Length: 180
Length: 180
Ligand SMILES: Cc1cc2nc3c(=O)[nH]c(=O)nc-3n(C[C@H](O)[C@H](O)[C@H](O)COP(=O)(O)OP(=O)(O)OC[C@H]3O[C@@H](n4cnc5c(N)ncnc54)[C@H](O)[C@@H]3O)c2cc1C
Ligand SMILES: Cc1cc2nc3c(=O)[nH]c(=O)nc-3n(C[C@H](O)[C@H](O)[C@H](O)COP(=O)(O)OP(=O)(O)OC[C@H]3O[C@@H](n4cnc5c(N)ncnc54)[C@H](O)[C@@H]3O)c2cc1C
Image: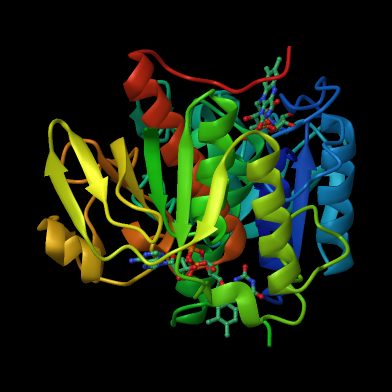
């Protein structure tokens, strides 16, 4: 059982996981391993990452960062999603995981949104400003919701943005993850 | 003498500057030095920066990243902005700086939006999906256009997103900064 299952382990999904975990939520990231930044030998435009590491290295750091605060990240290709009336049952080849909320950071892959019959905006998932889809308790971020042309920092930022509003919705008040 | 003048040198402005500069544009960032993240002793939630640097250090790294690819970043408070000869004239300590486009990454400060008569949306500047304001060739990003609750990665991502669409507008074609 999880508070939130994030489908997609690219920049948007891993960034969302970091924020959700820091908000005290039990979060699991299920990733199919096809992030578009994976083959990049050097990412020179992720503001602040001055060593301009490879896409694989970027993803490794993002995963490490999310785990540092409690997030779980596991390889997995979701092939099914069932609304059980209170919780979503997400199925991969390994089995099933349950969560009250879903956050789709699946790039352009229509698999997830089609299983849920989500309303679309062009070839992407339709959402309101904060990332809420047509289906209650289902959110979307990054390229999945039209933040294109896609870029790593754009997706990472949107993943955090949608996560922050998911937390705000859950808590019943504005959520800010600010340090001193 | 500038393709774009970015007002505000916080995460959104510096991220936008990095992308604009990498697009080959002449970009100038004028910053008042009041970034909200500057006082943080340790930023623990900027996806990927595992060393969790102070807000001051983060800003220095973002500035370095933008300068690395050609952006000029300097202290300065923008108070006067006129539209003449098809370009925006900005008064500065070094004389008038002219630009074809203006990008406001000024957080919640309503001073410039009010002077320019920009259409508002709540406590922020109204924009379309890509960051275009009600004033042609004037864009906005980050907290300035309502990406709140504000966070460094959220503003950095939005700055890049708006910059990418600004370049797309300038070139008349979807722009992408991807490694080959
Ligand atoms: C050749 C190329 C070069 C690029 N170079 C750059 C560059 O230099 N700089 C830059 O900033 N951007 C670059 N990009 C773009 C960048 O990689 C993307 O913008 C970024 O990866 C988008 O992040 P995202 O989280 O939205 O999606 P992605 O990182 O693509 O992640 C989507 C994830 O969801 C998973 N997923 C989808 N469906 C399922 C499912 N059913 N079950 C489980 N998991 C699923 C995928 O396997 C994947 O890991 C490049 C892209 C390409 C194609
Ligand atoms: C106490 C505190 C703690 C925080 N801790 C965190 C944290 O741990 N993690 C996190 O992710 N976020 C944190 N934040 C929020 C984070 O700092 C903001 O989300 C981020 O700085 C927003 O970036 P921005 O680019 O939108 O605006 P800002 O960084 O606020 O930058 C706006 C910039 O524009 C300049 N400017 C405005 N008007 C003008 C003008 N007329 N001429 C020239 N320059 C102008 C300002 O001087 C400023 O430098 C914190 C905020 C506060 C207040």
